[PDB]
Amino acid sequence: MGRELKFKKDGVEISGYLAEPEFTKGPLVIVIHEWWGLVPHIKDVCDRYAREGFFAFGIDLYKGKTADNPDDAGRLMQELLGQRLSEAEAMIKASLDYFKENDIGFVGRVQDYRIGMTGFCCGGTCTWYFGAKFSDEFSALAPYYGLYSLVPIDFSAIKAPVLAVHAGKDAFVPLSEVLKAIEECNKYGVKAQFLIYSGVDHAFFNDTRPEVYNEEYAVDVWGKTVEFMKRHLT
Amino acid sequence: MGRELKFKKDGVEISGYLAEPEFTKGPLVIVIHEWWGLVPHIKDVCDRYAREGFFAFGIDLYKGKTADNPDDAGRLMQELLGQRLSEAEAMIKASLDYFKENDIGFVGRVQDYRIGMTGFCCGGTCTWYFGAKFSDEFSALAPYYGLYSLVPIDFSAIKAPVLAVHAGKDAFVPLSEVLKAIEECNKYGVKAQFLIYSGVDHAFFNDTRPEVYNEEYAVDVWGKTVEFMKRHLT
Picture 1 (cartoon, rainbow over the protein chains, first blue to last red):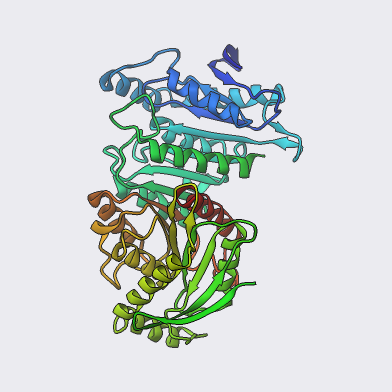
Picture 2 (spheres, each protein chain N blue to C red):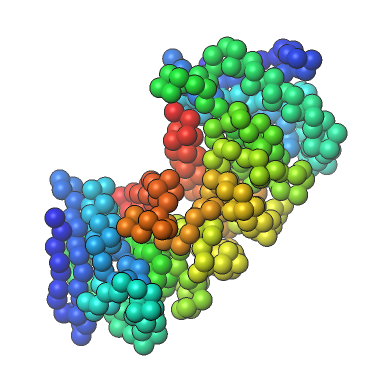
């Protein structure tokens, strides 16, 4: 089952796609879209999480807007990260509050909420950023190929374990930037594992983009990601 | 319940420890020791592989010698990787030939041999080096925290997928060296995934060395390694 949510809470508009497991009362994963916005591929990822026993909320951070080309997509992303960052923070916070009020993410085995977050591209940046901002709320973070140069990621504040996925030939994220993030995690004692796949580009997980998709590593990284989310959230 | 193999083949003396799975006839993994030599910890690793369905051969590359301190260990390692590298190569090749003659590592599903190789510290270096030297013989490589600057690894020759495990605070392997390896893999089309664990030291997998062992990441990396070896060897 997947449903479109749209409602107001604490003065902000929450919208996105919620995939729910069959019967399983599982953990929750927040899934953050790329710079194109909340498109079908992201909803598909949410469905895939639900088939593994997780509630998955593909939150819309673009207020219903999507882009099909880099120029418009870059404008939406720069607006989100550079002008509406406070608002996006408030949407994340209100979403978390909403799910907890509805018992979504409550895990019987531990008698507590277990909430993860993952995202791709700008959604990877957001995973890091929000994971630091809301460090009491998340039990696992899985940022895929986010930029570290767009917004200040406060590595000192992160409390969750992190699975950080990167592409070896990423045209947007130099390896030097990945190295700097590793050194910050070393410095602050962040339990971050960095996975760097040789020879693939940015967005290699996106099966709808044949110019960058890599099947071998997309299958590999999905296996690793589900294992990691299960380890920390169930 | 493994066996100590000792025999001569093609002019070189082979010795090591062979762990065998029960109730399953599976792939082979060659396991290469650290600079201490073929000590109980390494035999334990072989046993662990056998419990997951693999034959595992902990080859001795030190001609029966072990070391309990860094000075003696460093001398044995420098001798292995300098003066006796050709001999070690011949031991690896003769081992492979021996197993194939005895049907060890033959996998029914693919009607062919599937042989992996893994190792730690100097054994990680060896896994890279021999994986390139004997490029057609290996179907998976899992080098843990080896140095890249001791012997010339021929990245251009590697044909197997690689799971390269590194420690984020490795006192012996700077992250700049890991980056150089990633760039070589990118350049030559090696299917290498690099996994860098923040905050841990060299030899963090070694549960017999409490000063560097890290349980959380040793458990994590074991899971990842078994999944990878199963994916490529069964």
